[PDB]
Amino acid sequence: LDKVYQMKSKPRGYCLIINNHNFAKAREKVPKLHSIRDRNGTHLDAGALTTTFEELHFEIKPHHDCTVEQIYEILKIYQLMDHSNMDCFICCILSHGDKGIIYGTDGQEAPIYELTSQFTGLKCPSLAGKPKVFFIQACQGDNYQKGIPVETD
Amino acid sequence: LDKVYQMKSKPRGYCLIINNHNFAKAREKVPKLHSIRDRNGTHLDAGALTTTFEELHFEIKPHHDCTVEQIYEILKIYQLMDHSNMDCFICCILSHGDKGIIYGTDGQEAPIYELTSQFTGLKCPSLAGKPKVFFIQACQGDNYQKGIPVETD
Amino acid sequence: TRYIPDEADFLLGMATVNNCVSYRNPAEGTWYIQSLCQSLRERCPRGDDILTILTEVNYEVSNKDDKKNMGKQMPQPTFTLRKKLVFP
Amino acid sequence: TRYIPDEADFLLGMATVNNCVSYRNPAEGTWYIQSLCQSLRERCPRGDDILTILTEVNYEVSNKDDKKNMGKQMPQPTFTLRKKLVFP
């Protein structure tokens, strides 16, 4: 026993799914990205997310191949909604990225902080006191994690 | 029945407690910190940490007013140590701080990342697969967390 | 009515620690998302708190290997929640 | 003999979210540490996992106030633990 976040609500809350795949803009624009591959496989991520959170009584709100601007535009929407009848809010992002940033489908970048800081208590009081979950799925650098040995577990 | 970190070892592990109080050093050298006050009250923190962690069968290892340099030296020690018969390692730092960095007693900066990274797997095999805890108690900037109303809980 | 800090009740689930890559198999999707969902499915019904599920995802993903560049991937949650977070 | 990511099994107990301050009453210690302990000595015997405890510390700290500048303090723990971390 201990306090738990109320999760009774009908739709429970929205579950954004910004799913980036076609990165041909970035390639064109941003020089240093001339070779970023398209994110094959996301479809699957979006699907899995969609189902699993549907079954959890959340109202999915997908969006595909979004430039950095589109992403902000989108968050600003849910940032401005009245989540008064909502019990929680989840936002998923699947795209390329770098040290503390996510990549718009055009090469432009958006600090994870900017997106995250959009739904604070002041910025969106209709959510104050309710869980705001974010699942960023992107790279955060170009260093392949190391990995050492040990048989425990 | 989810996996659990093993904690049986006679003295579970070391519990470094770098506690800085006297910042006269700082005040005296770095200009922009001319007015940083002494952390009056840390001792109480230190004690509490000492007590409670001792009861959890942890070997305390206090250190007072350590300059940045000293801090590194200290960690360096526990870094090269052989925690083979240790099940865990806790490190507490009480001091002034700023965005992603804590302050030595000399007003010098120590990126929290620099500290924690001292104990990776490559940097400390004796601890591979073992819980490494860090409790930092400093400031991360000069803002004030504005509060918002709600009355849920 | 009462007061709580501006940034309370947040939960960030990074698929990887900083300066590092995260993997995506065009075949089945990504190590993180796929593993996050899989676990959510098998655990939420039971009653497992999201931190718990997120921990397991840290596990499963850790056992994956990019044999080639002998590399790994370590997810990394960060949270401000003030109550257990479960999904009935 | 298995492999795990270089950065695994960590746990940072930040006292405050970035850019903000932390509170220390020169008459009883810092909100965070004090709560950390109190919660530690309390929940640990009950066998509660650390994330669970840290969550509660998140709670307790949230209800504190600094009327002078109508301030708050938001602790924020980050982690890479791969299994429940209990302190028997």
Image (tube, coloured by chain):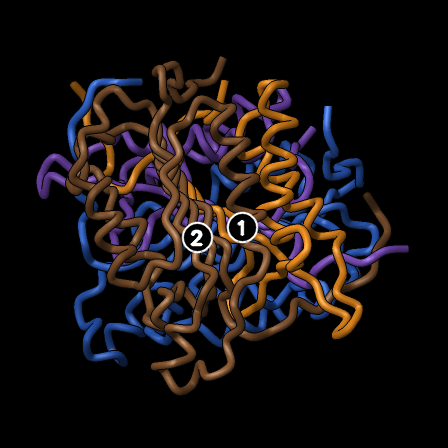
Chain colours: A blue, B brown, C purple, D orange
Q: Vertically, is D50 above or below B45?
A: above
Quadrant into which the C terminus of chain A falls: top left
Q: Which of A71 and C50 is in front in this view?
A: C50
Q: Which residue is drawn at 61% across and 40% down?
A: D55
Q: Observer-nearest residue: B18 or C37?
A: B18
Question: Could you tell me which residue is drawn at 69 percent across and 39 percent down?
Answer: C83
Q: Is residue C26 left or right of residue A13?
A: left
Check disc 1: other Cα within 10 Å, few if <14, some if 14-19, many if 20+.
some
Q: Position of residue A90 (x, y in %)?
A: 60, 50
Residue A25 is left or right of residue A131, and the answer is left
Q: Quadrant of residue B119?
A: top left
Camera-nearest residue between B27 and A88: B27
Q: In which quarter of the image is residue A99?
A: bottom left
Residue under pointer 2: B19
- Would you say residue A61 is visible in this rendering? no
> As drawn, which residue projects farthest toward the bottom?
B31
Q: Which chain carries label 2?
A: B
- Residue under mark 1: which chain is it in? B
Horizontal and vertical percent position of residue C25: 27, 41
Assign the N terminus of chain A to one quadrant of the image.
Answer: top right
Identify the residue shown where x is 40% and y is 39%: B133
Q: Which of marks 1 and 2 is nearer the N terminus?
A: 2
Q: Is residue C7 above or below residue D60?
A: below
Residue linked to disc 1: B43
Mark 1 touching mark 2, by CB under 8 A? yes
Look at the numbered disc 1 and give the secondary structure of its residue: helix
| Residue B44, position as x, y percentages in the image | 58, 47
Task: Describe the element under mark 2 as helix, strand or loop.
Answer: strand
Type of amino acid at the residue the image marks with label 1:
His
**Residue type highlighted by circle 2:** Asn
Residue C24: x %, y % from top left:
29, 44
Vertical side of B131 occupied by D29: above or below: below
